[PDB]
Amino acid sequence: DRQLAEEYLYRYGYTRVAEMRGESKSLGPALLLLQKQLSLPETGELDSATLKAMRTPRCGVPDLGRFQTFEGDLKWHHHNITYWIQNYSEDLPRAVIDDAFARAFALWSAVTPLTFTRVYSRDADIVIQFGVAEHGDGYPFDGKDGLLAHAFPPGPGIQGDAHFDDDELWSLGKGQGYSLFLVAAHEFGHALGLDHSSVPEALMYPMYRFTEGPPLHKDDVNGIRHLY
Ligand SMILES: [Ca+2]
Ligand SMILES: [Ca+2]
Ligand SMILES: [Ca+2]
Ligand SMILES: [Zn+2]
Ligand SMILES: [Zn+2]
């Protein structure tokens, strides 16, 4: 359990922030940062709630800090965001996958001055890929469960892109599997410039939770209103 906690705190940025605070050795300061960021009781202990959180499938984007240094100011500076579905999981029919991505974009288009347009080339702003383990960007996926997907903030090249771990069973969240619609809606939030939310019910909260309700909450809508 201590191994899992050390890796989780490293991967998602908590260990680095604790180091920058001289805090540095014991796991406690980093755990407190994680509890604050995930809205868990702030105990500073590797307790049952925190271990349960660390074991929950989630987005692979860091919570504090970023994957790397990125180019530009991390928002788009044009209004018609193009996207390319580069490949497909075989878990769902192609038409269902296409429609899941279109619906996830429709969530954001209603609450932003952006439009989303499907294209068929690498020139797209948002390139959408399914992959497993190392899949071409040096941020490898991890097999079944754990990390589900990740995305990159607006900008050139890999920036704006969204990747889905095809070692997950992709469905619409009914019966078995993870909802491609919900995870895509979350990842497209990053591809527009949003970070994770600390509100557990918000779409941009990092842990996966299935819901049949409307995916956007106030924190998500106000996040994108406070960007564009
Ligand atoms: Ca597949
Ligand atoms: Ca891109
Ligand atoms: Ca995974
Ligand atoms: Zn995320
Ligand atoms: Zn990737």
Image (spheres, rainbow, N blue to C red):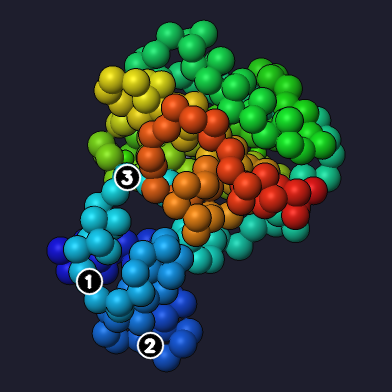
The mark nearer the N terminus, 2 or 3, is 2
Quadrant that contains the N terminus = bottom left
Image location (x, y in percent) of residue 81 = 75, 32
Residue picked out by circle 2 = 23
Decide if residue 147 is on the left or right side of residue 103. left
The mark nearer the N terminus, 1 or 2, is 2
The residue sitting at 42% across, 32% down in the picture is: 211
Give the CA distance from mark 1 to mark 2.
16 Å
**Figure check: 53 above or below 186:** below
Q: How crowded is mark 2: few (under 14 residues within 10 Å), some or many (20 or more)?
A: some
Image location (x, y in percent) of residue 226 = 75, 55
Q: Determine the secondary structure under disc 3.
A: loop
**Figure check: 17 above or below 2:** below
Give the CA distance from mark 1 to mark 3.
18 Å
Instruction: Name the image quarter holding residue 78.
Output: top right
Residue picked out by circle 1 = 46
Residue picked out by circle 3 = 57
The residue sitting at 24% across, 76% down in the picture is: 45
Which residue is more in the foreground, 38 or 149?
38
Q: Are marks 1 and 3 in contact (CB under 8 Å)?
A: no
Residue 125 is marked as: none
The residue sitting at 52% across, 43% down in the picture is: 203
Instruction: Name the image quarter holding residue 149.
Output: top left
Q: Is mark 3 within 8 Å of ligand 3?
A: yes
Q: What residue type is labelled 2?
A: Glu
Image location (x, y in percent) of residue 153 = 63, 49
Q: Determine the secondary structure under disc 2.
A: loop
Q: What residue type is labelled 1?
A: Leu
Which residue is more in the foreground, 152 or 123?
152
- Give the residue furthest to the bottom: 22
Q: Which amino acid does label 3 sit on?
A: Pro
Query: Total number of numbered labels?
Result: 3
